[PDB]
Image (cartoon, rainbow over all chains, first blue to last red; front, side, top):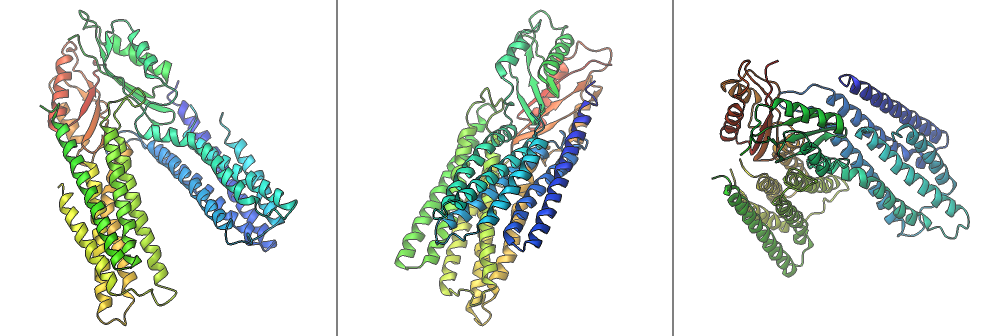
Length: 291
Length: 291
């Protein structure tokens, strides 16, 4: 009954992504009007962060819509790699935002006077954690979809930066002769953001480089296929994934000598085994008689 | 005799790349010592451009060396996608250099006085074309290797920028009340550089997205496969390339009813045809009896 199962998954993913996008836009407008009645550009400065989050989500939605298209004559496989590309784009945007914050901090640690803000820094950090914790529960997930995972990683990075800014504002508020704690918090929590993004970066790079997914081991699959009756060897067992949840395989069973007619049965057994017990959105196998 | 042929091409590509790298290093040293006796930082400014070119070539060499490794249990295919990644990196660095030039020009078009240099601008442009025209013949190439193609594209972009700077400097030299033409040439030749990089960007993106190579049409291959004796249909004919020159395929021949024993012959015929008449560094086909 898996013919239409994936449709429900993409519908849920799209619904969650549009809900997140409209929530981000609503928070954007709310913070903008709040800053307008509070005539402060520092509050408006978070509009850029909301912009990059919303742009990443919009690009993800476009990539998913394109991926829903049927394969063409130029792309024999589907457009599922567009979702991976959108994930890389989102990671690049969060890295760019972290780099901008890092440059602002490195300019903060020198030139003196540190451009003191005060209480207003606490408020923009208080809403940063409050907004991002809502998005974290929305994109919780806990195979999973790579798009929502990338959105959740972006939300977690934004939450880490927000809590770092909150901590820095609090330590500045009490005993304000320190006046310097903000750049160190910026550095430490930028490192933490990199730690958060490490796993998704590794998974995406492995996906692009035609490596096996991290949740599959070749030795176990090879032994399982070798357990099939009338199988002599597995010459090559290439495995790669178009995207998270859509992983294919190429298999090169060699037949037992003296039994070459029983090739269709072996092919069906291998196909059914691979599909049912490893996912294998589609798999193709090639049989060779004994040499 | 194709078992050891490809070794010769990788050896030649590596030799050419090291020759280009050492030529870049020698020109770097020559221009650096030349600037020291001419005590001008503008001459030293091209050291950054030679740095990015040399770094791109070095990353390409590392990617090729890694690609020469045998497939592992995490990457069932080879590391050939590292060469494609290095090509994207080279494109990204040339785009970054163009963006830095564009930002400098947009700062020149305003704030007045345009930071006049004069004759010394002609010299750094005269050696820019002379250096790049030499390696343009070196990386002439004219399937080809993607690494040398990316290096040649980078060299061509650098040559275009150099000739643009030369034209702007010559325009400034005569009738020097104009004094404005330099950013205009910068914009026009940045657009030309983007035009040069368009084709390699498109090819690399198609390679990553699991699209068929631009020099292959599925319909012709499908008709050729259908021309094979004892073939009823081609259910699916996936084609993708790990890198330029290494393209694989997956084929789903269905057998003519009443003839199922003659499956090995059909498989061998299809494999030989695909390999010899389309390249197909490796291809795998799966046969199904009539339904």
